[PDB]
Amino acid sequence: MATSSEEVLLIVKKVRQKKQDGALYLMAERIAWAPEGKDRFTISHMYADIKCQKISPEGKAKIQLQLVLHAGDTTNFHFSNESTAVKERDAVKDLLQQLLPKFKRKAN
Amino acid sequence: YVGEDDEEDDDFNENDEDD
């Protein structure tokens, strides 16, 4: 919210969000992402609003992850960093699978 | 595509399940 989620636990690079490349930064209580060329994060979602998460497997020209919210919305993250995109996808996934259920509550 | 147009987002595998 606005206390511990101001610290970045996971730093991700070259991540495209909505046809725009940038850097992703996962915080204690929220997932944030800053677009390249900008000084501010245009992506700020609380793990409490995230229902689930998808990870796009190999076979695609890119590695991806997506924040599926219970709000009926989905935040897709295109990992364009060839260097660690796969592992990055995995770490974002891991940390979220770690973090998400600790802040959210099933709709059932 | 319609709605999501980042590029290709279909083989997207879930993992958190139906929360």
Image (spheres, coloured by chain):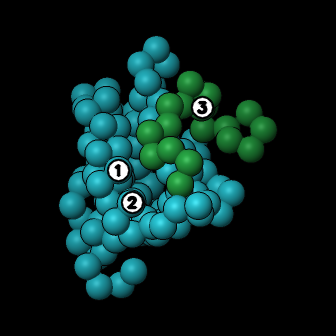
Left or right of B6 in this view: A34: left
Q: Which mark is residue A97?
A: 1
Q: Position of residue B7 (x, y in %)?
A: 61, 31
Tell me the amino acid under the disc marked 3. Answer: Asp
Q: Which mark is residue B9?
A: 3
| Residue in the image at 30% along x and 66% along y | A27
Q: Position of residue A85 (x, y in %)?
A: 32, 33
Are discs 3 and 1 both within one chain?
A: no
Q: Which residue sits furthest front?
A: A108
Q: Position of residue A14 (x, y in %)?
A: 36, 41
| Residue in the image at 25% along x and 28% along y | A83
Image mark 3: chain:
B
Asked if the residue at tag 2 contacts the one at tag 3, i.e. Cβ–Cβ closer than 8 Å, the answer is no
Chain for colour green: B
A82 and A47: which is toward the camera: A47
B17 and A40: which is toward the camera: B17
Q: Is residue A37 visible?
A: no
Asked if the residue at tag 2 contacts the one at tag 1, i.e. Cβ–Cβ closer than 8 Å, the answer is yes
Chain A rendering hue: cyan
Q: Is residue A91 visible?
A: yes
Left or right of B14 in this view: A103: left
Quarter where residue A38 is shown: bottom left
Given this view, does label 3 or label 1 mark the residue nearer the observer? 1
Measured Cα–Cα span from mark 3 to mark 2: 21 Å
Tell me the amino acid under the disc marked 1. Answer: Gln
